[PDB]
Amino acid sequence: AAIIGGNPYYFGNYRCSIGFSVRQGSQTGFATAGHCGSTGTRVSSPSGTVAGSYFPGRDMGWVRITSADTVTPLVNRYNGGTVTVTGSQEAATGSSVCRSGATTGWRCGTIQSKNQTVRYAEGTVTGLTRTTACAEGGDSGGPWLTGSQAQGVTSGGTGDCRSGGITFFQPINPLLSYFGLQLVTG
Ligand SMILES: *S(=O)(=O)c1ccc(CCN)cc1
């Protein structure tokens, strides 16, 4: 099947959301949150393995997939259709931004503050961008877009999408750099 940002993937007892399709030389996969699974973790739908994961400290990872699935430059818009990712030009503080994830679909907000530190129960994570968008469990790893420009993957936050909350993302460019990944674009 097509790898599409915002769609679910599974491992053991858990669900996270695909971030962005990526390539590493001849290999393919998708960016995600580090906390979704440590290096070597097997995943299903799509079949893959966590090829890299830095969490805590950062919250960045990627999953290498198999020939049974195909990378796309697409993100699920959760209204029947998709958004095409054309690059990863970083949006400014104050910009609108939207995220996609398997539990709450498409949700939007504003980028409030960058380089934020959050003391998660598993350990402290730095370098995060705080937004006013909401998220819920299952949405983690999912992509953030300002227009057609990739911003990050969902790391954490508080509250929910019924009553609202705040949400943190791991910026995408540090993730691509750390793991030596190329973003799949259209
Ligand atoms: S995960 O990083 O999308 C995530 C986001 C938000 C929550 C809200 C829990 N209070 C949980 C998991």
Image (cartoon, rainbow, N blue to C red):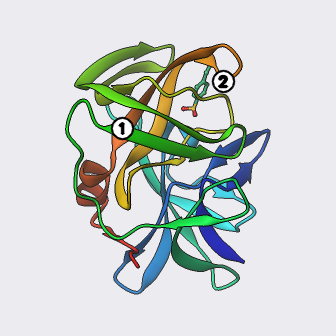
Residue bearing mark 1: 96
In the picture provided, is 108 more to the left or to the right than 139?
left
Locate residue 54, reporting x and y percent.
38, 42
Above or below — where is 6 with respect to 119?
A: below
Locate ligand 1 by image quadrant: top right
User: In the picture, residue 179 is in which quadrant?
Assistant: bottom left
Measuring 32% from the left and 68% from the top, which residue is drawn there?
Answer: 181
Which of discs 2 and 1 lies nearer the camera? The answer is 1
Measuring 67% from the left and 13% from the top, which residue is drawn there?
Answer: 163
SS state under label 1: strand
Tell which of 82 and 114 is nearer to you.
Answer: 82
Locate residue 167, reporting x and y percent.
47, 25
Residue bearing mark 2: 161
Visible residue check, residue 37:
no
Measuring 24% from the left and 49% from the top, which residue is drawn there?
Answer: 174
Above or below — where is 8 with respect to 81?
A: above
In the picture provided, is 6 more to the left or to the right than 120?
right
Tell which residue pokes out farthest to the right in this image: 13
Label 2 CB sits under 8 Å from any ligand 1 atom? no
Tell which of 26 and 114 is nearer to you.
Answer: 114
